[PDB]
Structures are given as C-alpha cells and as structure tokens.
Amino acid sequence: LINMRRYRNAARKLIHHYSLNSTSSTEYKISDVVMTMIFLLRSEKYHSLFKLLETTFDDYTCRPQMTQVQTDTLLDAVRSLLEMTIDLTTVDIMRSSFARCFNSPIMRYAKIVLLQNVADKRTTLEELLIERGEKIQMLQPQQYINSGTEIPFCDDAEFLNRLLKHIDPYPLSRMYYNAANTMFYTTMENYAVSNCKFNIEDYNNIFKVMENIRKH
Amino acid sequence: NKVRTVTEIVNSDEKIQKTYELAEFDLKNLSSLESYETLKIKLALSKYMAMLSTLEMTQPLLEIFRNKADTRQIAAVVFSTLAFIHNRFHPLVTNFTNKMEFVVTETNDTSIPGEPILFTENEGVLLCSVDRPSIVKMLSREFDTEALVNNCNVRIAKTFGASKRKDFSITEVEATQYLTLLLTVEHAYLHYYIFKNYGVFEYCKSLTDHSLFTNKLRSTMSTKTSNLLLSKFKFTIEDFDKINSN
Amino acid sequence: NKVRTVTEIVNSDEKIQKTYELAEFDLKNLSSLESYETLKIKLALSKYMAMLSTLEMTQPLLEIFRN
Image (cartoon, rainbow over all chains, first blue to last red; front, side):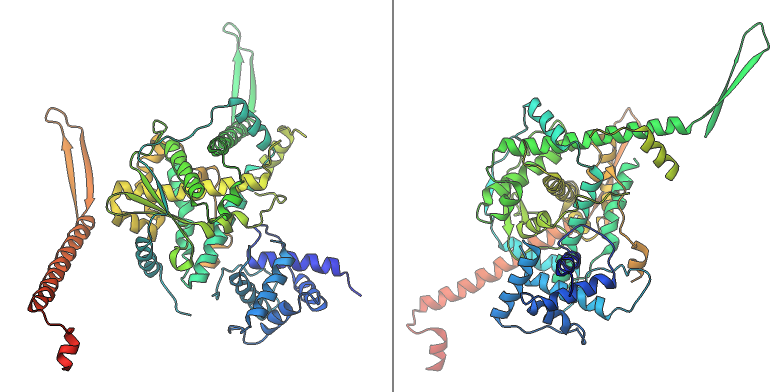
C-alpha cells in the first residue's frame, strides 16, 4: 500500500510549481515526480490527467486531441485538485513542463529554465505591438472620467494607524518576493501563449533601471 | 573599518588610547535605515489601502477584478492607483487634469504581454488599456506566506541586536495583492510619463526596451521624487547568466 | 534624425539645452499625408459614383456590363 495522502500532497505541490499557480519556490526531486505520477495512476478521479502526462513520455512535441467532454473532465479534475480560475492554457503549460521534466536526464543541479512550448508561428514583440495596438485602437472606451477630479485620499489617522498595526507583522521581503514573482510568471505565461520570445534581458533591465535611478 | 582616540591632559603627558571598531556603528546605521524604509513603505501601502476603502467598494479587490461586468469599479481603482503614484512623484498634484478614458481587454489577441496596463491617445485624449484577465491571474496566483527571503557576521549581529514582538480581512495575501497592483500600476505610470514627456515614438521605444527608463526618468525621479517602490530591494533573475546563454 | 535647442538669457550664461528626436514629427507628417491622400482618393471615387448616378441608370454597374 501507499500513503495516498502524502502522494497527493507532493503531487499538488509539484503541479502548482509546474503550472506557475504558486509563487512558492522549493526543492523538487525525482521522488516528488514519482509521488505525483503514482498518485495520479492510483486515483480514479485523475485518470485522464495521468493519461495526458503519460503521453508526454513519447515525442511530446505534439498537441493532444480531446473531445469537449474530455477537456471538461480534465479541467474539472485539475481544478478540484488545486481547489481554485484555471484554463486549458494551464493544462498545456503543465503538459509542456512535465514533458520537459520527463525527457530530462538525471542530474545533480536543478535545471533552471523558462517557459517554452505552450499554446507554432514565432512572433516578435514588435509584431505583437503593432497588431495588439491596432486592435486596441479599434476598441472603444468602456468607461471614462472627466478632467480634473480629485484623488480620494483617506483622512482617518486612527484608521491609518489601525491598518499599520494590522500589517506590521507582514515581512516586506516576503511580500516583495511574492509580488515580483507573480508578475514575472504572469508575463511568462503571456509570452508563452503568444508564442513570442521572452526578453529576459529587458525584464532584468527593469531592475537595472530601478538601481540606476536609486543610485542617484 | 576602525578608528582610535587619545585622551590627554594639557599639562601632563600621560595619554590614554582607545580603539573603536566601526562595524558596530555600521550595524546601527543599517538597522536604522532598514527600519525607516520599512516604515515608509508600509505607510504608503496603508495609505493606498485606505484611499481604496474611501472609494467604498463593497467587494474585496480580487472579487472586484474578477467581476468582469463592473468595469466602473475597475476603472475607478486603476485611475486612483495611477493618480496616487503620480502624486507620490509630484506631491503637489492631487488630480490628473486631462480627462482619462479606460478600456478593459478580454482576450490574448487584445492584450500585450508584459504590459497589462498601457496607454494610447485617440488623438484628443489618453485612453488606458487594462488586461483584467492578467490582473486576475496575477492576484489569484497562490502566494508563499511561509518561506523567508535573503555577510553572515552582520546577519548574526543584527539577529542578536534587533528585537522581536510576539478586525481587518487583510492577510499577508491581500497585502501582497495590493503591493503587486501598486507595482504594476507604477510600471504603467513610468511608461505613461515617458510617453507624455517624450512623445509616442519614445513611448513605443520604451515599451520595446525599458532600459531607456534609466535616463528618461533618473533625470527627474531620483532627484525630486520619492524613490521607486522597487528601490526597496535589489531584484535579480535566478540563474540569469545561464538563462541568457540559453 | 535629431536636433537640439539652447535657451539662454542675454545677461546670464546659465543655458538650458534640450534635445528633440525628429521621428515624432516624421510620424506626424506621414500620418497627415496619408490621411490627406486617402481623403482625396475617396473624394474622387465618390464623385465618380455620383456622376454615374446622375446618368441615372437603373441597374447596378456589374449588371449593366453583363447586359
């Protein structure tokens, strides 16, 4: 027999990381992958996801074909597992990530990678800019405010103090880490879905700019 | 490094020499600066939360952004954040002058990766484009409320010197959500500032490469304006060099 | 390409230099010319359609040429 609960927990954590649904970062290992796959196999509920991932053992550079019922079942299973919302885009992201992991060879140093092979034609940032901007200009403003107005600043100093107390035990370091990684992962997902190369250089140039402004 | 002092009486030659290691004062200074910066940032975050409350929207932030129908509240929140950042850079400004338009995209072919909030004029007035799906995705991504983030000698010294102390729906998760929204709107505001003050071509070039931000902003930001929120920490991509080589 | 301007007071030597990138004005000019040409061509086409209507032929153009 197996500790299906522990298997499930490891599976959930690994799936979260490989679907970029959690900013949490931790070590992972072949033990964890095996936990995940065994849990999926044993669970009647998740047989479809098990089949999906098992198919990654092959060339894995392919788009699985599913009926609408199959896709709905898979999405329901994933959403029940992670308790969230989700998307077949996330399904494909997990498929690609797990395929890369399975095809990867045993190693001593965890392979740091970026998102790749999600959602055929490679598009540049410039082409995306042109097309998206044209479509946006086509779009019309859903709502607007008039000129001037006034920022509605709060006034209750006691209220501000209460909020300050409520937030004091929150570590700014952890909050900053979580926020930055959230933004980074969402940008990664957008790029991968768009099939446009992610400019790691410019993404880091953002922080370079932050530092260059700070130093002055 | 170190210093030393000598005491001596005018009429006598018996002098007493003492030596001081500046590391202690360095620790004092670093702790003071860290505490001051933490207090400033928490004050700003609380102020942002408080003004959003002043708007008096019943739902919480994430629910607001999930409710696709109520574009009114999305626009209100976005504009309020943008104006707050604008004032934080120009405290004397409490409005935004020119009226503002808003649109909430709903599709990938309508959204631009890496710039969920952007700006474009209709040749008469500026329109702000919002990627509500992306905002929802960011604010919904599960956050880590457990792991910690980070010279060992000064680390130990701070550990042993500094102390610790053992009805709002806000948890660290919601605080993180607010901070993420603020940072995103700050990025968008920097883009918009470069646009307004350097032309649409410069705005497009910045979108292509943010590096121009360095000069186009530090010319005015680092001197007259409160430092960027991100300035609180130095950020970096894990395994950046190998990733670049990839 | 680019240009720059210098402001200075007659009695003072404190001068302020600003730089301009002509690409913005180039975009303005190109958009203006494109719009003007589009308007001219559409005006001519509308005028042509209108005079053909003035001839007052019942059928549409393609039907006319098919008959």
